[PDB]
Length: 102
Length: 102
Ligand SMILES: COc1cccc2c1C(=O)c1c(O)c3c(c(O)c1C2=O)C[C@@](O)(C(C)=O)C[C@@H]3O[C@H]1C[C@H](N)[C@H](O)[C@H](C)O1
Image (tube, rainbow over all chains, first blue to last red; front, side):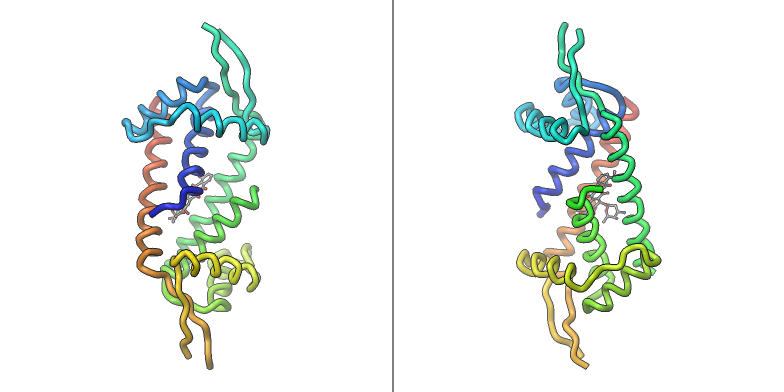
């Protein structure tokens, strides 16, 4: 079994990395992820929009419009910084664990 | 760093400790302190809080071994969950790298 809180986290990481590659709109994101996952992850629009409201509510991402009009989502600098801390944070965890194996 | 994220990390480390072998609270705090070379000094209360949840979820059990000490064990479900979870997160790493090919 896997904690649902944990799959929700993974999906967040993947999404944030997509915007890290560059700004994008929802349909392009699921497509990009569906491809990169070779088909195992078909994200549903409804739950995905639900997640993006939280991130914008956290200022981690912003949104805007551009044409063929589509609403694009941007990785904010605050989002950029948080991702750095998180990866650096999680990097220390991997080191803690490796030491434990001694 | 999200406090939510530190609790997850703290959970991962503790479980990886018990994967090394059954242990008691002060032994676990010591092992983590050493493995982090002093950067993570967990207080007794936080482990009890976390272990109460894990014991209730069947992820760990406890037992008295001797000079009395309360030992904590990672159950079979816990091992499987750690296995499944680590497999899970490994899949994410590929999805992301594929995104960079994209
Ligand atoms: C891109 O880095 C991240 C950025 C933000 C959040 C995260 C992560 C992240 O990498 C991450 C994980 O790698 C892992 C987890 C996680 O929550 C995050 C993030 O939240 C959860 C996990 O600890 C389990 C088993 O629950 C396993 C996994 O670590 C992997 C690699 C470790 N070296 C260790 O072997 C562990 C058991 O599995």
